[PDB]
Image: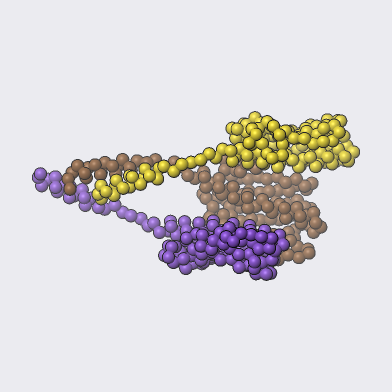
Chain colours: A yellow, B brown, C purple
């Protein structure tokens, strides 16, 4: 062994120890929101079916407790998605809101304690809102 | 040659022979599970299609033996993924379970002999479970 | 200067001239295959899109000659990767094979003149094969 090889190796080590690293948080922050809505959107179909068939609101709940000719139970647990929690509460007058609240022990720091919601007016119009940042909100709701 | 250069080279060799090395097993242990579910999830689409079209269960199998107007064969071999083996067995009553068992001759030591499963209740609800550690289980199932 | 220092230096030189060197060929032989498949896998998406949209096979080629409403040209040159050459030839009946042939003037000696292939059956099943050694074949194909 000589000093030339060792010095060249030391120099190449320092050269390699210079690669830059860009940001990688917005990607996950957007992927979380792209999944939350994709998971909590289909419930509108069951809500509309239950409201148009004949049964009134309130009885519409979540979980996995079978079904009957009076109450409706969509086949998803309140904590099926480990990213957050889902909550539904349809009033007797048809108006209601299905909300998804991000959990702090699973979701990302930016999307922590944030809430998305889909509301149904009394006449029968579906709107949606969220509390996340503008760049992280999906391309289907406001803020 | 002198003793100064040789001693400096020997000292620099010992200095370089001190770089620490962190852990690198959890990465592969999690990547294996992230691929297992991603590979064995899409079968639910074919299962639901076969159960809703008209054909009964049981006949639903795996492999590559073409298809007809009675039996269904999803286009994947039972050992397509070298990490483990897949097994499906839908009962005549619709209830069934698609399982993925990790092999010992390919999978990692931690994820060896572990089994993931996706079950379909009689009424028509999809659940999933696994036997891996909590930190290695994907963010879509329990333990 | 004395003889003690010179003899000690000569002895330390011989001592240092004894470091062993392990093998380092399998690493590159496996890295080449890990890159070949990673580069030539995504073409299946374009193949399936072109076969399911409406246009027939044959017209599907490679290079960079723009696109139109009849022919498809995936944005990669036949020699984009300097490790080998890519070749696609989809038949009119949908069946085809995308192959990657390693070049002798760039690839390693072990992975020289070897060929990987991804075939599409007539019914619509994707299989893959290779001609490399068992230990160098990726964990997604046979031999």
User: Where's residue A54, x and y in %?
Assistant: 90, 38
* C110 or B88, nearer to the observer: C110
Horizontal side of B19 relative to C136 (left or right) equals left
Q: Nearer the viewer, residue C141 or A5?
A: A5
Q: Residue furthest left?
A: C2
Of residues C79 and A87, the one drawn nearer to the viewer in this rendering: C79
Which residue is located at x 64 percent, y 59 percent?
A: C67
Furthest residue toward bottom: C92
Is residue B32 rendered to the left or right of residue C21?
right
Closer to the camera in the image, B99 or C127: C127
Residue C80 picture location, percent across and down:
51, 59
Numbered circles on residues, count: 0
Q: Quick check: can you spot residue B110?
A: no
Residue C22 x/y as whole percent: 35, 55
The quarter holding residue A143 reads: top right
Q: Is residue A95 in view from this perspective? A: yes
Q: Residue at x 68, y 48 (%)?
A: B118
Would residue B4 appear left or right of C28 to someone viewing this image? Answer: left
Residue at position x 25%, y 44% in the image: B9
Q: Left or right of C19: which side holds A109?
A: right
Q: Relative to B90, does residue B18 appear above or below in the rendering? A: above
Q: What percent of the width, then of the height, locates residue C29?
A: 45, 59
């Amino acid at each position: 062994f000589t000093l030339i090889e060792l010095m060249i190796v030391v120099a190449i080590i320092g050269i390699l120890a210079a690669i830059a690293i860009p940001q990688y948080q917005n990607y996950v922050a957007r992927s979380e929101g792209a999944s939350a809505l994709a998971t909590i959107n289909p419930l509108k179909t069951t809500v509309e079916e239950s409201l148009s068939r004949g049964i009134a609101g309130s009885k519409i709940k979540i979980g996995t407790t079978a079904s009957t000719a009076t109450e409706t139970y969509v086949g998803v647990e309140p904590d099926a998605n480990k990213l957050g929690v889902i909550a539904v509460a349809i009033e007797d007058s048809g108006a209601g809101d299905i909300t998804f609240t991000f959990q702090t022990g699973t979701s990302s720091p930016k999307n922590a304690t944030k809430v998305i919601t889909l509301n149904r007016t009394a006449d029968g119009v579906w709107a949606c809102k969220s509390t996340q940042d503008p760049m992280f909100t999906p391309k289907g709701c406001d803020n």
